Image 1: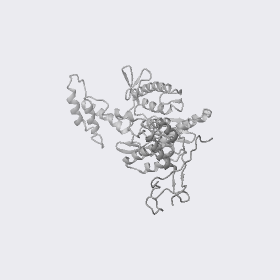
Image 2: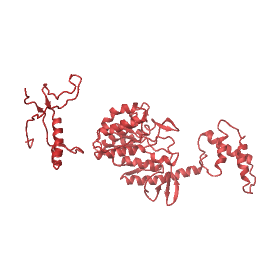
Image 3: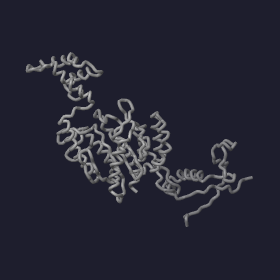
Image 4: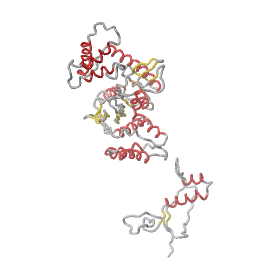
Length: 95
Length: 345
């Protein structure tokens, strides 16, 4: 297999969520939400990875080397990370 | 003339060159210099027939011809000294070609022909250029290099610090015909070194020198790295430590690349930073553009590589020749690395 483990999951907003896409000329909301390629909200995998990686680095302070291999070093990255995140697709929204 | 001949004599000749400058006294200078000599000849009662009015004239006649001809009057001792020094500089030049694992093809006097590996070529030019000027680090054979004075066991001998020395490096495939590699080396320099001008710092002004250039060539790519940047190449003992000062700038840069401290993309991104570093005439601003260009395509976060900052604006030109040289020094430093790295793959 190309991937050792493949772990899909769901991301449940416990509170209101705001992953920023930064201000832009054509938005009309000053701080908008990260959008999809067809309009819906989404979480860029760069936001997921960086948020989860920063979480793990302080929750598991002894598994640094195990996290750094799978999620990439930070000081001197002599190689590529082994784990990938996929952009979070909006599954269902409360209406 | 004034610096030569030091002692009580200097203030005498200091006044003889004074009474010349704008078509001066015409032997009516004795008055200023007779006092110098006649108030000196009584320091010992042995003057036989020293006609002081003629003695100071003949001296005034001597320096006149020197300044009229604009050249030192050549004597045998002037030749024998330059000739012998040229043979001692040959000795130290052979140790350097052996130290850098090279093969001397001929080295007679000022000339030299060697085959170095592409690796030891840059630091060879660095040491060879300075060793020619007498300045140098650790002894090579039984002779040391003491700021323009080769020394063999307490015996100090003069070298040629002022004389420029151009270099010509052809990076050639081992299978290239040796007829056209040697021909190019004598038609890349001896008619390419004759046409290359750069902006030299002369007495506070910025003039255009043309010699001492160290040309590099790798099948079409050409680079020129001036070795002086100051037109009287040495005028004081502090002038030595910046001869070939651009070479170690390339040497340090090359060092930080193979250690992965700087990506080789450094050589490929300079093009966009170049137009700003060219147009910028405020040196506090350029020392930040090259600091930015270095750190952008750097592969680490603790590489602090400086450029001597006297290298901002050289503008090497060339008069209508089939050799295309970038018209700025930092660009030539990039091409020199591409040539050195092109001959290692």
